[PDB]
Image: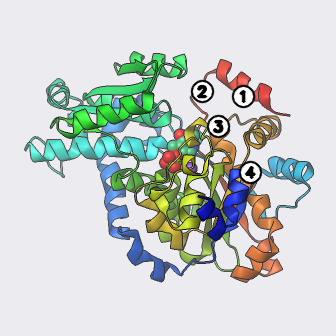
Amino acid sequence: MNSLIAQYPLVKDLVALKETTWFNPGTTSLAEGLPYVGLTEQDVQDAHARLSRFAPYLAKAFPETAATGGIIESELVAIPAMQKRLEKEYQQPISGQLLLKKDSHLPISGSIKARGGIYEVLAHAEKLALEAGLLTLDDDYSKLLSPEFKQFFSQYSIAVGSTGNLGLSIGIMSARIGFKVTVHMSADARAWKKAKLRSHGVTVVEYEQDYGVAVEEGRKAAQSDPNCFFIDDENSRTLFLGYSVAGQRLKAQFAQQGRIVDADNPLFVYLPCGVGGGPGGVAFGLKLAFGDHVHCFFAEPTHSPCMLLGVHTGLHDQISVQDIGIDNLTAADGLAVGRASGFVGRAMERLLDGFYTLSDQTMYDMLGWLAQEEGIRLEPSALAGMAGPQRVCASVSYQQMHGFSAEQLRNTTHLVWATGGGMVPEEEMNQYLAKGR
Ligand SMILES: *Cc1c(COP(=O)(O)O)cnc(C)c1O
Ligand SMILES: [K+]
C-alpha cells in the first residue's frame, strides 16, 4: 500500500487525487494481443447476428426503434465548436478532428448500457426459449411478443444491484420481455430512476443502509436460486460482447461518412470506465474493426481510478481504490466503481494505450461547455472521455513511444465516447449545468 507506492510511484499521485495520465508501455500488435482476450471475432459476429434476429422483435416491442428496423445504435457527430472551446479553456491544441459518439442517446435506455445490458437480457431470453423447444434460430422473433411468451418469460426472474444505467437498461428490457425483474437500489438514489423502473413494472427494492451488503446478500440468495439470474457486471463476458458490437457499427458509420482510419489517419478513442466492461468491450470491437490503427484510452474519476490502479500495478481486481485510501466518492456516479472487472484488465491491457483520471469539476466544466457549444446535454460520467484528446496531444513521450509523425497527428480523429445523458430529466440536468464554471 505504501509497499505499493514504493514499487509504483504513480500511486502517490492517485492517493493525492491529482489528475493523472498513464501511457501503457506494454501495448502489442493486434495479433500478439488477441490470444489473451479469450474471445474472438466469431464471438463478436455471433452477437451481431443475435441482435439481428431480435431486430423484428425490438421494432415492435419498443416502437421507438421501428424507424431503425429494431436496431439500437447512436449518432456519430462532429464537435469542432467544442474542440475550439477546449483548446481555449485548457490552452492545449487538439490535432485533427474531434467527434462524439452519442451512446448517451441510444434508444430505449439512453446510455451505453443499451448495448451490453440489453444484449445480456436478450441472450438470456433466447437461450431459455431455444432450450424449451419454443423457438428456433430461423423463427421471426416477433413471436416473442405473444401473451404465451410473456407467460413463459414470467417463469424466470432477473435481478440487478444498480442505482444507475445498468439497472435502468436491464430493468426496462427485462420487463418488456416479460421476466420478473428486481432492481436493488440505495434509498439515496434519485427518485426519477425509481419512478421510471416502476412505470415499466420493475420491482425496485430500496435499502436505507448497508446497500453494498444488501446487494451481496441478494447475489448469494440468487446463487442457489435456480430461476433467478442476478446480473454480474464484474464477470459477464456476455455484457462485454454486447458492448463490442459498437466496433463494427462505428466502422460502418466511418465508411458512410467518408472518414478514413489507417496508419496515416489514426483513430484515438476516449472511453469512460466504471468496472471496465463497457469501455473494454467497445475497445475490443474497435480493435477487431480497425486493428493497430485505433488507439483506446480509458478515463476515470480521480476518486475512482480502479482500472488504472489495477492495470498499472498488475493486481487488477485484487486491489481496490479503498485499499489505498481513496474514497470512491464522485459525481460521476456511473464510474463510482472501486474495484476493476474480474477479467477485462487482463483481457485487454495489451490492446489499451493509456488510462487517465479527471476531477469532478473538470467533468462539470466540460459538461457545461458542451451544452453551450454543441447543444448536447450529458451526465457527468459521460464527459470523462472529453479530457482525453488534450492528455494525448500534450504528451511528446506518448507520441514518441508510438512513433507518430506530425502529419499522422494532423490526420488523427479523436472520438469521445459519450455514455449517458439522453434520459436524464430536466431537473437533474439543470443541476449538472449549475455546477460547472
Ligand atoms: C456503464 C457506464 C459507463 C461504463 O461503465 P463500465 O462499468 O465500465 O461498464 C460509463 N458511463 C456511464 C454513464 C455508464 O452508465
Ligand atoms: K473505473
The Cα–Cα distance between marks 3 and 2, rounded to whole angstroms, is 18 Å
Mark 3: amino acid: Thr
Whether the residue carrying mark 4 lies under 8 Å from ligand 2 is answered with no
Mark 1: amino acid: Tyr
Q: Which residue is mark 2?
A: 424
Secondary structure at numbered mark 3: loop
Q: Which of pointers 4 and 2 lies earlier in the amino acid sequence?
A: 4
Q: Which of pointers 3 and 2 lies earlier in the amino acid sequence?
A: 3
Q: Are marks 3 and 1 in contact (CB under 8 Å)?
A: no
The Cα–Cα distance between marks 2 and 1, rounded to whole angstroms, is 10 Å
The Cα–Cα distance between marks 3 and 1, rounded to whole angstroms, is 13 Å
Q: Which of pointers 4 and 1 lies earlier in the amino acid sequence?
A: 4
Residue found 29% across the figure and 49% down from its top: 53
Instruction: Mark 2: give few (<14), some (14-19) or many (20+) Cα within 10 Å.
Output: some
* 116 to the left or right of 226: right
Residue 77 visible in the current orientation: no
Mark 2: amino acid: Val
Q: Which residue is mark 1?
A: 432
Instruction: Give the image location of residue 257, x and y in percent.
Output: 64, 59
Q: Which of pointers 3 and 1 lies earlier in the amino acid sequence?
A: 3
The Cα–Cα distance between marks 3 and 4, rounded to whole angstroms, is 15 Å
Question: Disc number at residue 330?
Answer: 3
Which of the image's four quarters has the N terminus? bottom right
Q: Which residue is mark 4?
A: 16
Instruction: Mark 4: give few (<14), some (14-19) or many (20+) Cα within 10 Å.
Output: few
Mark 4: amino acid: Ala
What scheme was used to colour the molecule? rainbow
Q: Looking at this rendering, what residue extends furthest in the front direction?
A: 3
Q: Which of pointers 3 and 4 lies earlier in the amino acid sequence?
A: 4
